Amino acid sequence: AASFREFASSNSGALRDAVELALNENGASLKTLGNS
Amino acid sequence: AASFREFASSNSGALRDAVELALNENGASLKTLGNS
Amino acid sequence: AASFREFASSNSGALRDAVELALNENGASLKTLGNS
Amino acid sequence: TILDTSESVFKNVQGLLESYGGAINNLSGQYRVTVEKYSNTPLEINFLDTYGDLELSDTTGRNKFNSVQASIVDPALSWKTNSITFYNSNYKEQDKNLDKKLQLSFANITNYYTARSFADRELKKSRYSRTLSFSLPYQFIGIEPNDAIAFTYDRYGWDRKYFLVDEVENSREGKINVTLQEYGEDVFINSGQVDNSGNDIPDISNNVLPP
Amino acid sequence: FANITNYYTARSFADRELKKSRYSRTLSFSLPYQFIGIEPNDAIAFTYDRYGWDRKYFLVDEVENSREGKINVTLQEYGEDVFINSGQVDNSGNDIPDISNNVLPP
Amino acid sequence: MKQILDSARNYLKNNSRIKTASLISLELPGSTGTSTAFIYLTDYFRDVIYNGILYQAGKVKSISPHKQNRDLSIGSLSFTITGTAQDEVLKLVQNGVSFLDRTVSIHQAIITEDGSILPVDPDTNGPLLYFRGRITGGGIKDNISTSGVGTSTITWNCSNQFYDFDRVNGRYTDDASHRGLEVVAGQLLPSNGAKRLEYQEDYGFFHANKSISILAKYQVQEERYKLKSKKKLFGLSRSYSLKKYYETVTKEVDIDFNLAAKYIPVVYGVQKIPGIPIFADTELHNPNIVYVVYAFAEGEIDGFLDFSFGDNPMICVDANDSSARTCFGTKKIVGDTMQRIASGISSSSPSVHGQEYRYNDGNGDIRIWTYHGKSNQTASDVLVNIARNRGFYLQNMNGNGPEYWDARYKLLDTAYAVVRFTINENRTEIPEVSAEIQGKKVKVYHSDGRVTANSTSLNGIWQTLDYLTSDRYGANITIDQFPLQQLIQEAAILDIIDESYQVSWQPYWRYVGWTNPLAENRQIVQMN
Amino acid sequence: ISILAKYQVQEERYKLKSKKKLFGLSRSYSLKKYYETVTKEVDIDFNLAAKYIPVVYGVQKIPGIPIFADTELHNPNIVYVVYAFAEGEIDGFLDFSFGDNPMICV
């Protein structure tokens, strides 16, 4: 697990991309948090 | 890294599930973004 | 894929950490959802 | 329906569909709309038709309810709001007396009796929590959301167990993945009701009584 | 503060929060089963010579039990001084009466 | 910490190979009647007996870890049982099943070399508990390979009592909700939905919805549907932006298109709150005489202290208010209270159940009856002696009889005030009404085993305990799950005396909540 | 509109009633935040969205968007105003409310 924590924290941007892909598909985005 | 980008983008839905599990555990959800 | 679903759901917290790292870097956080 | 055209079209459509449970599809390329239904002649299927991968999941705790209130705008209240609510004794007995209230608001419905009859649908539906997922070979091509499946599988004791198709994924090879949502027949049947005419409150204001 | 109205109490509590905020350190490790029965907000004194820590004081902040018995924990540092207030001074000189919606008599 | 018996601590310290059994007591799903079976299971390699209850062996496969931290959470678990046991599949897949609540408990037993269970918990002198809670869901996974072995497994998912953080469990002023109406055979009836059986009698709130539409005809266009908000400063946290917080702090609401306003608030300590109107009418012969009923607060409150009409309080704030305006007594040093208006002398006491108070503003009579909302309160006798005479105007215009108001309008468990306005040239409209009250009585415990249950408490623990164990509202947690001998130590912490200040610096003290300015009123924490 | 304001009490001089007050609730919303965002009125000053034309199906009640105001030259007591209401060919107007007072008796 800990290795996966270290890896994921080292690769965080790609996860954010994938999440934005899903939410864009439904029609939403994290940027609402940026403004909020 | 790039392989991990490609993989994650190909498997985006499972990440969204895991995030929803954590946030539901604390008592929150992304659907607030859907309405917002 | 299914193995990756099972793994990610078993390791959900680390993904949430990585997302918070990215969003904190830009200056945002999921806790806005907690209050919202 | 009243639509504010400043809302983005996607969201206006979504709320409009949500008002009557419809959903739309573009599998097979034509735009198609499929309301939920109780169907007399569902497509029969058996476990052995599938690839054999099967998963059942049930989410009673959040999703289930046993009493409800709904809110509407009503001309008999001068287009003020009205708040329908009711309980279900049998459901509260099947649950261990735990009270749990469903909250609703209907944007586009104003006939009180229609709103009540629809809320009863939503309450009854909420008892049927089960969702099921599996994969099908290419010969079953042409399935869509809100098709009616009867599922038969002896080991579980299921026998023409009734489901609606809720998600679909086509592939270049032809293998089809599906997910089913359980419903009963009784979802689509309303009780009796009673004449509500005794409370047509006239919300007069901004007037001065004559001498 | 939503639920506190005694000014002096509110001040004495805010002083706590300020003092607490100086103690940022958090620490994580795992324990064998014999230490069973720990809970959040138990008080730990930690001793480890290489760091120079000597009855270094912590509160338990997260716990995870397991079927095997292995316990993971996390500690949050605090000092003693967190729980002690200074003096204060009588604030009675500003009891502003917010009268409104009234008409002076002749 | 829970203190284990030290024999166990020593045994565990010595012995290097240990045997442990997990023992599951489980309520059966889908008892359609309230009576339910239980099943008992273990993961141990053979069946085991405890309290003479025999726990079966072999069905269990695994149990998840279990995490908690300083934040509130559902504390969820899962555990798994073999998918091949035909009975358990049938236990899921029956159609008529419900398990929205079913209980589960998981004991953890050290088993010694003679096969006895080691004593560990000094309360029961027995095995520990690993977990306890309620079922929330489950699932089945069947994997068939084309070739070689497949697998089948059943998962059960469990959680604490907060497993639906969406649950709203208040009360709000609508008869069908309060009585618990359901439709049968072409009429409405009271049924099980009432939060308590007695409520089915209570035709309270029956007039409520129309009453506001009547009341508007007596108010300036500023107010005709407005209401003041409740709990204006909700707690700030780093989740909020400073701006968005203070910009969402809001003083007022419109009841038109707003239902949340009509939920009854709960109060502990001393607070100021607006009245929810639930009935308005005029005396038939003299439309200048107006009766109004305001509901205020859940439960038995310690009592009303004061009323504000608009923002004008009856009691003078200080000497300057007394100079500006007619008012009785003073809040500021003496802590006078509305009891003074009936006694003619200074008093700190709250109201008494059912007295008539005559606030002579010098602008025609205001009269008040106050009911503290205690159970077994009757309907108000002044209203009854009108409706029984058909004295109400709208009563006579609709043609209703005494059914319009009688001994069935009890308004149980609900504090309410009857206001009799007089309208004249010097009071051309009804003002807004809000009041200051001393809150709900709570069951403070004592280490000696008493339960005083007499008064409000400013202590946050006893406040939380009442809110949790309340079932009419709140979380509906049974008291037997709490360790009283622990909680009392926590209160003995939280009531430590502070000395950073002295009581004489606080003139307000009676409104602050202290019952006496001289007895120590100082504790690290006081909550309203 | 800047002309029309000279004929209205300070209560109203730029206010307008909202459209589609009850937008659809879903589990995405908190109950509170929903009913607290349900809003009766808007100010056209600094608000452009108010001036989008709504679409209607069935029967509904809606506020008029003013697009022209003027007075007869010889007799300033005579005021013409044009209100736009709805997109497309409607089946027709049924009734008017001036303030909340409808012409037809309730």
Image (tube, coloured by chain):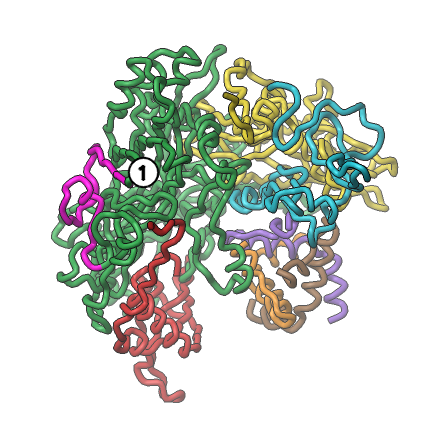
Chain colours: A brown, B purple, C orange, D yellow, E red, F green, G cyan
Query: Can residue E94 be seen at all in this image of the molecule?
Result: yes
Furthest toward the front, the residue is: G74
Query: Can residue E34 be seen at all in this image of the molecule?
Result: no
Segment colored magenta: F333-361
* Residue type of the residue flagged with mark 1: Asn
Q: F88 or F263, which lies in front?
A: F263
Magenta stretch: includes residue F354? yes
The part of the image, by quadrant, that contains residue F278 is: top left
Question: In the visual, does G85 lie left or right of F444?
Answer: right
Return the x and y of residue D45 as percentages of the image width and height.
72, 28
> In what quadrant of the picture does the N terminus of chain F appear?
bottom left
Question: In the visual, does F436 lie left or right of C27?
Answer: left
Question: In the visual, does D122 lie left or right of F517?
Answer: right
For disc 1, the neighbor class at 10 Å (few under 14, some 14 to 19, many from 20) is few
Q: Relative to D74, does residue F238 appear above or below in the rendering?
A: below
The part of the image, by quadrant, that contains residue G21 is: top right
Residue at mark 1: F363
Q: E69 or F189, which lies in front?
A: F189
Which residue shows up at 43% across the image and 58% down it? F235
Furthest toward the right, the residue is: D29
Question: What's the chain of the residue with tag 1?
Answer: F
Magenta stretch: includes residue F209? no
Return the x and y of residue A26 as percentages of the image width and height.
72, 49
Return the x and y of residue C34 as percentages of the image width and height.
53, 56
Q: Secondary structure at mark 1?
A: loop
Which residue shows up at 68% across the image and 26% down it? D150
Q: Relative to E92, does residue F446 appear above or below in the rendering?
A: above
Q: How many marks?
A: 1
